[PDB]
Image (spheres, rainbow, N blue to C red):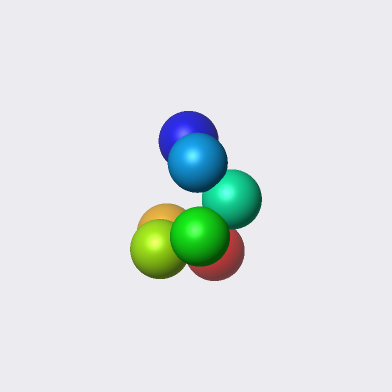
Length: 7
C-alpha cells in the first residue's frame, strides 16, 4: 500500500 513495509 505505501511501497515500504509489505514489499
